[PDB]
Image (cartoon, rainbow over all chains, first blue to last red):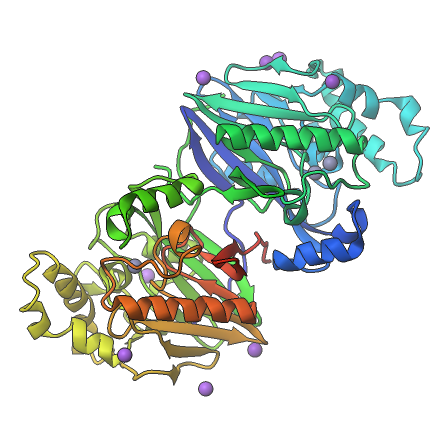
Length: 294
Length: 294
Ligand SMILES: [K+]
Ligand SMILES: [K+]
Ligand SMILES: [K+]
Ligand SMILES: [K+]
Ligand code: NA
Ligand code: NA
Ligand code: NA
Ligand code: NA
Ligand code: NA
Ligand SMILES: [Zn+2]
Ligand SMILES: [Zn+2]
Ligand SMILES: [Zn+2]
């Protein structure tokens, strides 16, 4: 016999993409009230959930993706650190267990500035990635880092999002390490930002490609696998432009389905990487087959 | 920047079931000439794999399952040790990565005696699990351990399967550590052996259950997910009784669909755990949702 260990495996998943090395890094999981946030009848998501063997508050993974192009070490999204509950902020640890040091990261690309994507930028009041530049969309930054917008926040108190994006990015801004880009942009060789606005004013997709092998890093372009693959147009109360999100999601899915390449998203079951094919009304997400990397 | 690490994470997946702890143990992966194995025209198989973004030779998982019942630590299947080439035999290492020691395993349940399941019983010339009692269906033992049956398989190195089983289980028989059962039989509390003969004469399913949460360990009841879930009728050349495997697979699938409980299988993409639901003609496998245990 033995005492139960009750600990999950290190939160990182290795995958080769052409000549690049991808490592999904889990920040952990948090239970979310799916029913209340979806723009569709409560009974409808409760049914979608049940068909996916999902329960009331969905335990959702929060993920970031490390890309090592063999020339640059780039991290896509950084998790929440301590901005979104006691159950997140595991990225830094997983990055190290993944075999890397925060100091080795050259660049950080932000899909959007929500707490669960920018919190990891800071370890206390010190840059968590001291030797990297932070890249995000200009519209994204002009929205969250806006003093005006903060003091102009609706459901006040819960405007810690503005405070949140600020404490996470300003330190790099003042260190002269924030380099915003505008929409579709060539970044480091092998990676490109594609403007997939809607979830937020400057939400960005990061397309990774090596040797004809592509991986579109979707950010929060999709939030609930149980309903948004089958019905791509269903949005949430968390999206800025519902119709923009819908249009961009359908474009992303159509394209990846047409091209047969990989996609990943911050909240699909960790590692959250897979292919996507057409299926009647919408799409069928196909998780990557398990594969050993030596 | 930094050199690419290129190593997969430890191959162990934690999951709680009632008061039990389940740890899927990856023994590695092996490529399988799947289109040659399935008993249907090659083009058909190849088309099914494609719809799932796959191609043969197909990287296929080989998994074993550790169950800590609190009072007992049992291992269901053990991987191949060396019997199948250098890409396997990692179950031992992964068990330790999982925070357990081979010497702590109390019992070992074998779904069947193919090499990729009993190989890990031995480490070199030594018992890998020195303090464990091994269990299997007597029909399985009578068949694989029969010097006669070996001397009746003209198929040069098919006798290997017979030798594999023998070399793998006789050290335990010789030590009085082998205890067969016949047909359905309650093993330690929380775990039942249910006959599922077909793949091999005594192929057995192990059902674990705690606090109403059920997990059926199906062994090799399914080999190619991209084919056999949509078509439970397709068999393979390694199946002893074709009709029987089909029947037992359908019974398992129909049962997990109506019960809505979890099922696990040695060759479903690591960790190979999920639920099953009927979809038109046949079934659809829904892999467990990533979950953090603390
Ligand atoms: K360090
Ligand atoms: K923009
Ligand atoms: K750059
Ligand atoms: K119990
Ligand atoms: Na730059
Ligand atoms: Na290219
Ligand atoms: Na030991
Ligand atoms: Na019983
Ligand atoms: Na029988
Ligand atoms: Zn978001
Ligand atoms: Zn998010
Ligand atoms: Zn097998």
